[PDB]
Image 1 (cartoon, protein in one colour):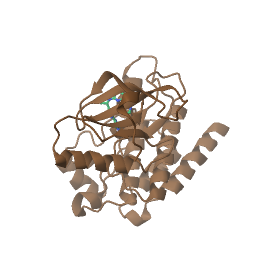
Image 2 (image 1 turned 120 degrees about the vertical axis):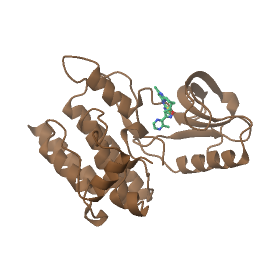
Image 3 (image 1 turned 90 degrees about the vertical axis):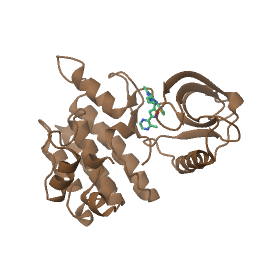
Image 4 (image 1 turned 135 degrees about the vertical axis):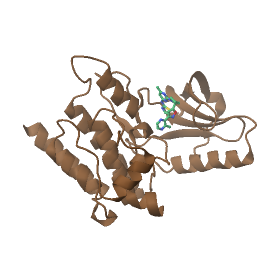
Length: 271
Ligand SMILES: Cc1cc(Nc2nccs2)nc(N2CCC[C@H]2c2cc(-c3nccnc3C)no2)n1
């Protein structure tokens, strides 16, 4: 657990209060090493006067986050758990959640979307590399969706990186086995990854839009799948359908998904 002195941490603005207590944008000194300097950070706080039951949950969250060191997984830089309020220090993803970033790219201008197909494919590659790491760690996320991913930039012209954020009812993202049997495997995360790349390729559309949570479980259990995104490339729709195979055993691995996305990216770039 990366113990960090709260004296080297400064809280500057409030990002929100949708987790344990509040999330702050701040700065940390020497968090990446003694002479590294001041770096921008996100700070997950646990409210002072929190119950023992809440402290243990915060401690669990810090233990899970300490296991992840990958460019496409949100990184925990340090923790302040000796005193109250408790802090979980994270790398700052200034662009916010991927769903909002996608929706704003579609709904901002008249000329066209602020994200091209090649920008979208690179978002899929970034997420799939994060999933390969998780599959290798034998970690099952349980909630892979665009709302649970973060973007490093807020603009649409700078180089960007998408990271898998907060770790796991979200019915539209759940595979059929999770819905009826409560089975949660890396192959059910593969189902969710296909839902997330559909979200990316539609620039933030809600899956199964005409349907409700009860209609979704009925429709999906009986073989019904999402309609293809408008002008979606064939090889991307091929991989999306592979991810939604009724049997988890028939669904491809994350290592295969990364290769197929990489092969499509090369096939697309050569044209
Ligand atoms: C414009 C911005 C940037 C940012 N950046 C962050 N960077 C790191 C953690 S939060 N956060 C935010 N927020 C708005 C709500 C509160 C805070 C937030 C979002 C997340 C998050 N989201 C998706 C997946 N996983 C996580 C942990 N956590 O706090 N708005």
